[PDB]
Image (cartoon, coloured by chain):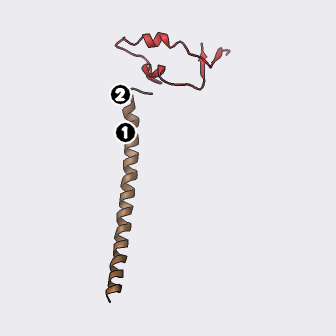
Amino acid sequence: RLDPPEAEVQIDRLITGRLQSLQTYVTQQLIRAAEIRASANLAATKMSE
Amino acid sequence: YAWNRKRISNCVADYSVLYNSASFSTFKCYGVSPTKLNDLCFTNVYADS
């Protein structure tokens, strides 16, 4: 609907929003993975002992 | 206080003037780019004079 010089503003807005969403998702996944890893280590110890 | 408004629908409007006013190196429109105006579909159009 718009032309190169005008579209760029909306393009930038959407880019910022979606980048923030991805960053939040990745951080949450990292924390959850750390928790699950701790649980897995405990389970391995339980098996061995 | 009695500006006349006409309903335009089921139509092809006077796109010709601005469509042919394309070789001009300058364009004067802010709501939407003039060039794209002839590659879209509108539910309804209002004209006021």
Q: Residue B29, located in which quarter of the rendered image?
A: top left
Amino acid type of the residue that numbered disc 1 sits on in the rendered structure: Asp
Location of the C terminus of chain B by quadrant is top right
Image quadrant occupied by the N terminus of chain B: top right
| Residue at position x 48%, y 19% in the image | B38
Quarter where residue B35 is shown = top left
Q: Which residue is mark 1?
A: A12
> SS at mark 1?
helix
Q: Earlier in the sequence, mark 2 or mark 1?
A: 2
- The chain that appears red in the image is B
Judging from the image, what is the letter of the chain drawn in brown? A
- Marks 2,1: beta carbons within 8 A: no
Dot 2: few (<14), some (14–19), or many (≥20) neighbours within 10 Å?
Answer: few
Residue extending furthest toward the front:
A47
> Where is A13 relative to B23, above or below?
below
Residue at (60%, 16%) from the top-left corner? B48
Farthest-out residue, right: B2
Residue A24: give x, y in percent of width and height: 39, 56
> Residue at left 40%, top 40%?
A13
Q: Residue at x 34, y 73 (%)?
A: A37
Percent of width and height locating residue A38: 34, 76
How far apart marks 2 and 1 lie (CA) works out to 12 Å
Say if labels 2 and 1 share a chain.
Answer: yes
Residue type (three-letter) at the residue carrying disc 2: Pro
* Residue count near mark 1 (Cα–Cα under 10 Å), binned few <14, some 14–19, many ≥20: few
Residue B10 lies in quadrant:
top right
- Left or right of B10 in this view: A19: left
Q: Secondary structure at mark 2?
A: helix
Residue A30 drawn at (x, y percent): 34, 64
Q: Which residue is mark 2?
A: A5
Callout 1: chain: A
Say left or right for A4 vs B42: left
